[PDB]
């Protein structure tokens, strides 16, 4: 009997070029500080474990042996290797329960190297994707540019990874990783810092000792850059309720090592939440964060490991019906005056469908409204069963007739309140991960 939900463990650890201690089980049990897992769940395995490392000094063979031993000790299950991929000292391991070996297909791996010349050679990202039954899953482990003064370079690294990491279905040619997966998890040493003056270091340390994180989180560069729509547009993160995970003295967690030294290039490392887990799932699909925290007992690195766990909705492929898009229009931020057409892509279609050109008019601010009227092709899904169709998504790309390049991409849920009824639909449109416009109109879904 096929599951409707699985549980996914995400771990991120910057190992600080040191080997791990003998026992790392606390990481995989979600024990320590923050939103932690209940003791009563300790022996219950997660379906999929995704382990991201940075500054990893081990061989693939050495680290795989440690991970499989740790999980065997916790669960009495011998986990199967789905994928492993390493770029320099940045690594991703995906392990799954053996009962899932025939549920997992289309495994892909890739990496991106960020920067150019002297910034090219240790920062970037690794990724894995696969299908679990009918559900596509993507996982990204990035190690972004270091240093409190380099937030804009981190945002540029993000944009490069999002654009160039080649995962998921290659037929989705208009779409980047932010639209190719039912569920996308993006984690790593993202290296965003708490932006307070360097002379406040001792004040920050006393706030951490009091477990008073609010005045530090209000200066966390990732939270402020996300609020300003500069990075991770349309991603989610669980609330942080654990101490900063960087930068610790090794072999204890009692001291933060913040002061400038020759070894840090005379940079301050004020305590920061460098180590993060974010996600982006298709609209209305079940995804719940069940833990988000840091370990307290793993002390070989200047970072503490971070864990996050999720309940994630999955579907079967189910191996007459109709989707009608009515009175639709795109509002674009572009100054271009080409004509545009749409492509509709979905796992529920045999192949993507191209629309005729829309009718351009000038909007209120002078910006571009592209009108599609009642002109859009009726989409014919391969299965009409409402238990299948209402769980599906239509990916939309708006493309230039002159260049055939996408100006914007979005996603529409078929999880409607009604069938055979005209209902409002809406997605933002993004391109290279930044907002380019909006798509709005009405839908009518025919099922059996």
Image (cartoon, grey):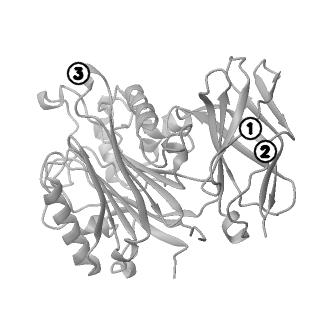
Whether the residues at callouts 2 and 1 have beta carbons within 8 Å, the answer is yes
Which comes before the other along the chain, label 3 or label 2? Answer: 3
Q: Nearer the viewer, mark 3 or mark 1?
A: 1
Numbered mark located on residue 118 in the image? 3
Out of 316 and 45, give the one closest to the viewer: 316
Q: In 3D space, how far apart are the residues under numbered discs 2 and 1 (Cα atoms)?
A: 6 Å
Q: In 3D space, how far apart are the residues under numbered discs 3 and 2 (Cα atoms)?
A: 50 Å
Q: In 3D space, how far apart are the residues under numbered discs 3 and 1 (Cα atoms)?
A: 46 Å
Badge 3: residue crowd in 10 Å (few <14, some 14–19, many ≥20): few
Out of 15 and 338, give the one closest to the viewer: 338
Q: Which residue in the structure is indicated by mark 2?
A: 377
Query: Does residue 412 lie above or below 386 as drawn?
Result: above
Q: In the image, residue 231 lies at what x, y percent?
A: 49, 35
User: Left of 127 or right of it: where is 383?
Assistant: right
Q: Quadrant of the C terminus?
A: bottom right
Could you tell me which secondary element the residue under label 1 belongs to? Answer: loop
Write the residue at 75% across / 33% down. 330
Residue 322, image quadrant: bottom right
Q: Which residue in the structure is indicated by mark 1?
A: 355
Residue 102 visible in rendering: yes
Count of numbered marks: 3
Write the residue at 42% across / 26% down. 152
Q: In the image, residue 335 lies at what x, y percent?
A: 68, 17
Write the residue at 33% across / 75% down. 98
Query: Does residue 199 lie above or below 251 as drawn?
Result: above
Q: In the image, residue 82 lies at what x, y percent?
A: 32, 62
Query: Does residue 315 lie above or below 427 as drawn?
Result: below
Residue 336, image quadrant: top right
Whether the residues at callouts 3 and 1 have beta carbons within 8 Å, the answer is no
């Amino acid at each position: 009997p096929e599951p409707d939900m699985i549980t996914i463990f995400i771990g991120t650890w910057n190992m600080g070029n040191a080997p791990p201690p003998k026992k790392i089980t606390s990481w995989f049990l979600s024990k320590g500080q923050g939103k932690t897992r209940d003791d009563s769940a300790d022996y219950i395995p997660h379906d999929i474990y995704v382990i991201g490392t940075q500054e990893d000094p081990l061989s693939e063979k050495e680290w795989l042996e440690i991970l499989k031993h740790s999980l065997q000790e916790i669960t009495s299950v011998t986990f199967k290797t789905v994928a492993i991929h390493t770029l320099w000292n940045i690594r991703i391991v995906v392990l799954a329960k053996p009962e899932h070996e025939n549920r997992i297909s289309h495994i892909c791996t890739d990496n991106v190297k960020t920067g150019i010349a002297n910034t090219l050679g240790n920062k970037g990202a690794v990724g894995v994707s696969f299908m679990f039954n009918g559900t596509s899953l993507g996982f990204v482990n990035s190690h972004l540019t270091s240093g409190s003064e380099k937030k804009l370079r981190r945002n540029q690294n993000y944009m490069n990874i999002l654009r160039f990491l080649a995962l998921g279905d290659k037929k989705l040619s208009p779409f980047n990783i932010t639209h190719r997966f039912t569920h996308l998890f993006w984690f790593g040493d993202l290296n965003y810092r708490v932006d307070l003056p360097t002379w406040e270091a001792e004040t920050i340390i006393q706030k951490i000792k009091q477990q008073q994180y609010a005045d530090l989180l209000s200066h966390d560069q990732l939270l402020t850059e996300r609020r300003e729509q500069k990075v991770f547009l349309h991603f989610e993160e669980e609330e942080i309720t654990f101490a900063p995970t960087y930068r610790f003295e090794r072999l204890t967690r009692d001291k933060y090592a913040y002061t400038k030294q020759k070894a840090t290039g005379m940079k301050y490392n004020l305590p920061s939440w460098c180590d993060r887990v974010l996600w982006k799932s298709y609209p209305l699909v079940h995804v719940v964060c069940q833990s988000y925290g840091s370990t307290s007992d793993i002390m070989t690195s200047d970072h503490s490991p971070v864990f996050a766990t999720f309940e994630a909705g999955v579907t079967s492929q189910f191996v007459q019906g109709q989707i009608e898009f009515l009175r639709c229009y795109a509002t674009l931020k572009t100054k271009s005056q080409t004509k545009f057409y749409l492509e509709f892509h979905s796992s529920c279609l045999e192949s993507f469908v191209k629309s005729q050109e829309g009718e351009n008019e000038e909007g209120s601010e002078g910006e571009l409204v592209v009108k599609f009227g009642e002109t859009l092709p009726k989409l014919k899904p391969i299965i009409s069963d409402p238990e299948y169709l209402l769980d599906q998504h239509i990916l939309i790309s708006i493309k230039s007739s002159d260049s055939d390049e996408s100006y914007g991409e979005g996603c529409i849920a078929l999880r409607l309140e009604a069938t055979e009824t005209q209902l409002p639909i809406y997605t933002p449109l993004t391109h290279h991960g930044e907002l380019t416009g909006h798509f709005q109109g009405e839908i009518k879904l025919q099922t059996s």
